[PDB]
Image: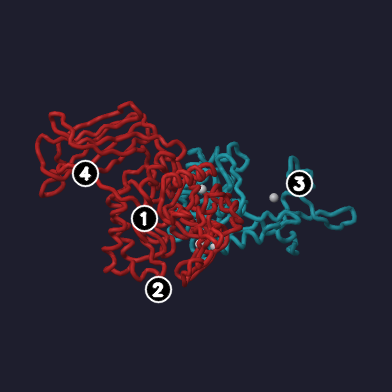
Chain colours: A red, B cyan
Amino acid sequence: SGIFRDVSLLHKPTTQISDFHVATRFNDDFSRAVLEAEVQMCGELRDYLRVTVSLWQGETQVASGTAPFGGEIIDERGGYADRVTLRLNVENPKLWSAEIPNLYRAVVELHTADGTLIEAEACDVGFREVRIENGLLLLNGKPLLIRGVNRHEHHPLHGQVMDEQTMVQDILLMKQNNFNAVRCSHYPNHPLWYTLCDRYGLYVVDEANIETHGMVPMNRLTDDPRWLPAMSERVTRMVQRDRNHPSVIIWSLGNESGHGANHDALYRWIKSVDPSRPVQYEGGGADTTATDIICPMYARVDEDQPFPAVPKWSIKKWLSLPGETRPLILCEYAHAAGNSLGGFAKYWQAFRQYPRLQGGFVWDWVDQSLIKYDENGNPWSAYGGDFGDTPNDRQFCMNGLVFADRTPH
Amino acid sequence: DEANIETHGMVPMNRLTDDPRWLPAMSERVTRMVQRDRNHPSVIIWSLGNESGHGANHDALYRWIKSVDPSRPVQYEGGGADTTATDIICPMYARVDEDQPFPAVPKWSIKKWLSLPGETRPLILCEYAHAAGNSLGGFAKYWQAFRQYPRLQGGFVWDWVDQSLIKYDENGNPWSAYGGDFGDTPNDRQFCMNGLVFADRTPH
Ligand code: NA
Ligand code: NA
Ligand code: NA
Ligand code: NA
């Protein structure tokens, strides 16, 4: 507990940019694209106010558009006088992917007609399309093969406080070891994480901070309408914060909270506000109506585990169950506790042979060990129970591919 | 119940079945079969024939059957075992786990075939486990898969009885003969024998 992430002060003019969404649509062969930027303001509306959105590729300006506030008619009462949408055409856009993280820069300027700048905001833009078609998750029209890993925010000395150096180190080790994707298990990450994934090139599953694993049954709270408000804020505020990051290609409703009606409601909310990304959730069987992707945890390659209500079918078998058509990507697999990863090759042989088996996220990146000091001041790796904490789950906090100090297992 | 239509020797296999001039002769082989056997409860599936590639004639006759008798599914293996002329994925000799990516007409692992993007049909092999002589090795691998996968609904072994004929030596003693033993040439020798039982129905 504590104030474990940055604290800052931001000054904004009274007449300000209060929000902006960036989207990129493409033609059939991705040779042409349109960047659509919806900008919202707060403060006093004036006819002389203007919004200019310009797009840059390095020091080269690719496009720019300007317009006064006033959106198209929405319903019987009119439209949003405090909003405006700019549309910019881009020919032969340099596409974003984990393979080639091409990025453009969108600058959003709030200014007066006479040319006086009031304030400017901006973001890195990655031109890419994410969509599920005919049962396959596609990125820019091509079927992905997720070489991912689950990554908790953990530091042996600083606990859950993240720093740029540690983030960069994790990303480099990941790419150097052929990983192209990461799942934010199981909450929105430090804001710099997304910036680094955008620039270095890694596919990200952004996950809502919702896990009620300890409830009995697991969905006791998620199926309770009285908890819908609290859950909704965890999902909606995540989307409102990270929707402009190209690295985020999939939204997750959380983790191990069973399957409740609140999940279906929030699943639809996301699909409604942001159709550019698929939504996944593993709770309640990995294939409920709240997930566009069959995303089981620890389902085996050939062996079925027919648990009542929430069976873990062999992944090859899962795909062809009567009426099933969705792609399958394990949100968690290959538990790396100590001397582990036996049978890892079996998953990959299957991933490569089956089009709809599009990978998974290994569990997990780093051991959650903490440093303690003996009588002589010598440091040692501690785990559950070493702090007098009880009850505890001892060494179960250590199942990463690398030690806490980032040394490889 | 399978229509008497096989043009295996043509090159390519669908040279005649894709030719509208052979539609008449083909249609009678399908239509007259249905007209004769449609009241038999034992018949649960209609087949358009065997190894004749996939031609437009197949699509036309497939529809004709669906139209006149919607009580039974229609299947046909030609042209890849999963064409628009079959309600059932019915390959011949597709293996359990191993793919055989032949050009145009691949024989995918049956487990993999089921989940190909957009595929939803059941899979029943019209032919599998070739029983030529000392054979049927790996037979249990098919059954383990049939039982685990709901949509893998079995298949038909190839085949029931050796097609050997009887001949008599100088002493009048009979012996089992195969291709070529009658002066017939060209011939495909012992290939006419791959049944689970000998011609006299003695079990292999
Ligand atoms: Na695959
Ligand atoms: Na663990
Ligand atoms: Na079956
Ligand atoms: Na034969």
Q: Could you tell me residue B195's position as x and y percent?
A: 70, 57
Crowd band around label 3 with a 10 angstrom C-alpha radius: few (<14), some (14–19), many (20+): some
Q: CA distance from mark 3 to mark 4?
A: 92 Å
Q: CA distance from mark 2 to mark 4?
A: 46 Å
Number of the label disc, if any, that sits on residue A11:
4
In the rendered structure, which disc, 1 or 2, sits on the residue that comes first in sequence? Answer: 1
Q: Secondary structure at mark 4?
A: loop
Dot 3 amino acid type = Arg
Label 3 or label 2, whichever lies nearer to me, is: 2
Dot 1 amino acid type = Phe
Q: CA distance from mark 1 to mark 4?
A: 23 Å
Crowd band around label 4 with a 10 angstrom C-alpha radius: few (<14), some (14–19), many (20+): few
Q: Residue at x 40, y 58 (%)?
A: A281
* Discs 2, 4 touching: Cβ within 8 Å: no
* Discs 1, 2 touching: Cβ within 8 Å: no
Residue that label 1 marks? A4
Label 2: chain letter: A
A272 to B140, vertically: above or below: above
Crowd band around label 1 with a 10 angstrom C-alpha radius: few (<14), some (14–19), many (20+): few
Q: Could you tell me residue B78's position as x and y percent?
A: 55, 46
Q: CA distance from mark 3 to mark 2?
A: 70 Å
